[PDB]
Image: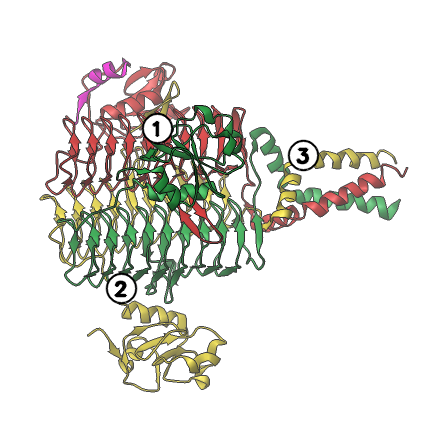
Chain colours: A red, B green, C yellow
Amino acid sequence: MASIRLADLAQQLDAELHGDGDIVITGVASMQSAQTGHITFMVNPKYREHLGLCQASAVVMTQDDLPFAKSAALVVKNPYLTYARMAQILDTTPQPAQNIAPSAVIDATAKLGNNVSIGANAVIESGVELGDNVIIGAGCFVGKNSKIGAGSRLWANVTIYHEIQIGQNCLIQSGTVVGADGFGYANDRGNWVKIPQIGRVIIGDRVEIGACTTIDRGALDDTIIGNGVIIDNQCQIAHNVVIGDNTAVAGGVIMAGSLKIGRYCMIGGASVINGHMEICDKVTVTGMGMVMRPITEPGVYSSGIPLQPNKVWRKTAALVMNIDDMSKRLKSLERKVNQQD
Amino acid sequence: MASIRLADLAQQLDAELHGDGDIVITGVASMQSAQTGHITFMVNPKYREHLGLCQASAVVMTQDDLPFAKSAALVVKNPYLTYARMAQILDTTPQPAQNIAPSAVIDATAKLGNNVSIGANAVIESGVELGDNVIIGAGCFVGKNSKIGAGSRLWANVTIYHEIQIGQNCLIQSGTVVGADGFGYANDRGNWVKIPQIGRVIIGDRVEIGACTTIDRGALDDTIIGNGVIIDNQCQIAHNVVIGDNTAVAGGVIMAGSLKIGRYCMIGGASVINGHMEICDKVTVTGMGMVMRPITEPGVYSSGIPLQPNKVWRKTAALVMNIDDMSKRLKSLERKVNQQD
Amino acid sequence: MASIRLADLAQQLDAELHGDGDIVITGVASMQSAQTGHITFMVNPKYREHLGLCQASAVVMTQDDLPFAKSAALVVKNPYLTYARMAQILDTTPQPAQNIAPSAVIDATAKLGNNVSIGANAVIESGVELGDNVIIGAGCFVGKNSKIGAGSRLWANVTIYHEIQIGQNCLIQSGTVVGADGFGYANDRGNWVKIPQIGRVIIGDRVEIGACTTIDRGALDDTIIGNGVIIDNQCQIAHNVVIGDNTAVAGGVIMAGSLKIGRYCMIGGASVINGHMEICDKVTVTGMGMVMRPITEPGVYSSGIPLQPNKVWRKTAALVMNIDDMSKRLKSLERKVNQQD
């Protein structure tokens, strides 16, 4: 199962074979570390200088690169997208579980599709439904009445709370928490009153969520993750956030309550986003974005003063904090020269 | 559970029932998605315009809004507050556990109060004391000699280290880690030599801690969390941090060791706070605040520049760096003007 | 058994006996709270006055306090240091586990050295290797074929993925997740296509990793953490990041994919570091550093505008955002003078 032939792979990748079609390929690697049996690629500009010393058994390349080839070669229009596909074909990643661990704790009321795997010490609460081909990693928790769509996989130690819905073909990395009670509290004077959070989380199809990420459930209504959304490690998604289709949310993003984010957005790492607010389609937020105001026009947005050497920074911070006195000095000369000629 | 008559409820909420009083109510909903049997509420002012097509059976409402009643309305002086309680009254949220699960691993030494329930694959180590009504969720870990007070609930997959003390009626969401070792190092020729951390963590009554938060143990003395404090998701509370009664801490907040924060503070999401520093009572640090220096006076403090479209941003950020250029030029200009004529 | 005599201690600790040689020494404690049985120290130069109100059986000390010594004392060159040694040898800090628990799930093909401990409900996958004296905490997951060197300790609820290699004498706190898929996706018609992440994490010797940290696997080649590295809570280290020997990373730092940090660095809390970049040796970045360009010169680097009273900040923000206008107004008038002769 590990290995297939170059010709057979060319067929599946839709590439023109140019070397010997019977090379036995065992895996993908990078140009630098590739050994015999490995296939590689260069999206690379200029690294075709060094194909002669690359030890890979075949190299996915562009037609323009072919003159430079020094081994079997697969010619395509897009070498990077071909890489994605062939790494899937040759994926070494295990599954989080296989079959049902005798040590799993499965409520008698839970409903299981065909070909479902549940790992050791995983806990499945009452009324849970898991579709066909679902895989639940070891140590997972799946709260009451939750639903997990066919094809979806949880890695080890994921926490899904109750009344959560998860789409098809989703992937959730370890340590992640879905549907924790939202940060919402009443008040008299001083001390707080907890408002039960009876909303849910609805997660679309083909959603990928990274590790140690937290997705709070909504107050009354739902917090919603659209189809094909990708979210990296350690994001905070507040109650009632809505994230549109194919939005990418990088690592460490902090997103406040009732934020609506359009489709095709790119939110950069460590961005902090104000809540009860809206960000339109096709907005891009640079790394460390401070998003206080609603974004109503597409395009790319940014904030922050990048790093500088300490000696230099100290002056910069000090003048910034006195931009006021520096402002006024300016208007005083702007007046001294206006009237007095 | 099952519903209750609108009247029964109106008493327990201290409200004026203007309408049918035998209307049956099964839960709470939003105006937008209410149905027959649901009670919604409003002080959402301008939303009296759309009340007629709201499908809720009853609405919580001030008296100024009483003339727009197109349904059984309930009059109070604070609606959100009324909600907050009816919500408790009509709570659906399940319990993390019921009973002692056969699969939970409980040291013969541990002492349990009355009617504690402990989830599946939970692990209670020796010397641990759990109070009356305490609920330990699935996959939880409670370390040696740790005491959890009456009424406190941990959700699934919480990890409590050894010698940690938790007060009464506390709530802790999944993935949260309490009592890990903090930064503790001498330096033996290039490499960091660890110093054992033997303090512990003390959490007061009625504390709510969100998911994937980390609260480090003290070095010798303790990390202390005051009563009625709320800490949201993925906050980092370092060693020896002391947080006062009733303060609120939003998500992704980072507190260095030895920080003391007084009562009734409100720390904006994503703020980073220096260590070995005190912050007085009644201080607000707004979102993403950079807290470098001690705060000795109540009020609101803010930090950082907001978003700008990339085009603008780059110009601004270039200009902000070497303001020492602008500073000198202004100084050089006013030098020739005033002094010289 | 659990305690030893002063005279003996003073000898293993390398200090001069001044006072009683036989009191029972249960353990270390601070000045404010020490008691009979407790040995404390005093690194302060001034607290020497309050030495008399301590109630403790022994105090480590400099010869310059010896006179003001209110009870038995130990004289050394560096107190803080001998404090480390005191604590290093006196602590009752429990081991994450002791021997192998009945509920631990161990695959038949896993390899265990001498005296390894595994905690309750810990799951050890096929092909895994545990060196001598290794300790796996309660609820941990160790993935297929992973290697954990001798002396190494995982605390409760740590997730190690497949093909992860960890060195010797390392320490990983709870909640942490090692070797999760990096954020790698090809975009095909606005749809993200998942690139499998088939590299590993390699972690050296003497590494200490805090709680709720995420360390991602490489796409193809590896993520590498060098010897003697310390990384504290809530950190995100992306795929293919390479962190050289003895670097220190404080809480909740974010490292983008394919970043290279040289050895001996000190990266302050909440710093955010751009990917595909190099930071040379001996770089210190103060906290909330916004690092987007490579660092080629050793030294101390900073960014950020410190906190201001909100009233003052509103003003500072606005002027800064319109810094273009006042760069113009400056030149526009700088010209006027040198043009009006």
Q: Is residue A35 left or right of residue A61?
A: left
* Magenta stretch bounds: A2-17
Mark 3 → mark 2, Cα distance in angstroms: 58 Å
User: At numbered mark 3, what does the secondary structure look like: helix, strand or loop?
Assistant: helix
Could you tell me which chain the residue with mark 2 belongs to? C
User: At numbered mark 1, what does the secondary structure look like: helix, strand or loop?
Assistant: loop
Nearest the viewer among C191 and B318 is: C191
A66, above or below A312, in the image: above
Q: Amino acid at mark 1?
A: Thr
Say which residue appears at 53% left-offset and 59% top-offset. Answer: B280
Say which residue appears at 62% left-offset and 46% top-offset. Answer: C313
Front label number (3 vs 1): 1
Report the residue that reaches farthest toward the right: A341
Identify the residue position indicated by label 2 in the image. C93
Q: Quadrant of the C terminus of chain A?
A: top right
Q: Are marks 3 and 2 on the same chain?
A: yes
Q: Quadrant of the N terminus of chain A?
A: top left
Could you tell me which chain the residue with mark 3 belongs to? C
Which label belongs to residue B36?
Answer: 1
User: At numbered mark 2, what does the secondary structure look like: helix, strand or loop?
Assistant: loop
Image quarter of residue C100: bottom left
Identify the residue position indicated by label 3 in the image. C324
